[PDB]
Image (tube, rainbow, N blue to C red; front, side, top):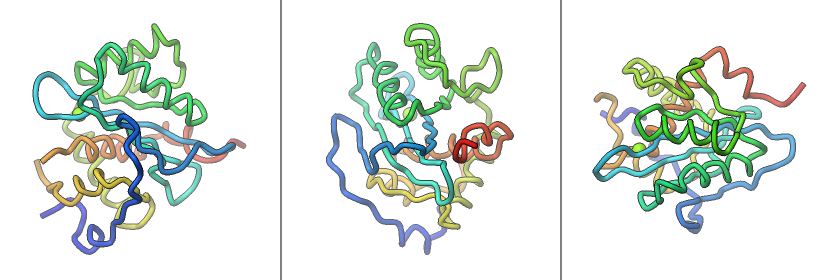
Length: 198
Ligand SMILES: [Mg+2]
């Protein structure tokens, strides 16, 4: 009872890139392409990882071009690491799940690093406000993208997590960061970020 149907899961495949201290790069940034990054931060104590997914949304199919995945990042430096990769991907907009750590990272990006491509649900929510409906609808959107071959997955750990991710409520941070992306794609504001500049 996986979210992604078995035949699709069986055809997923990864490019086995070297881990650069948590950063996995499948495509370099390219001129004229438009990206988005989604961030699922770990919170509190336990066995979870921070997961930043960077997706090329210039045109279909969308592509997973890089991932940052770590549970050994110093809290003091996580905003600077995210900022580095957003700047790399053509000053990438970012959509952060606003758990306690995500609220702090979003504020650091806005106030300390002065990054001005933060996707915000509202003036007081500097990212994706937590809700149950955003998870469910983001999962449905992600299922359709992967099953219709409209989102290409390259990363080994992401595929491993997709193969065990249940259709209802093992690590899942790489999938949950893709669920944030799926939810974004259902919103009116996604048209501000997707597509070539006109
Ligand atoms: Mg997490």
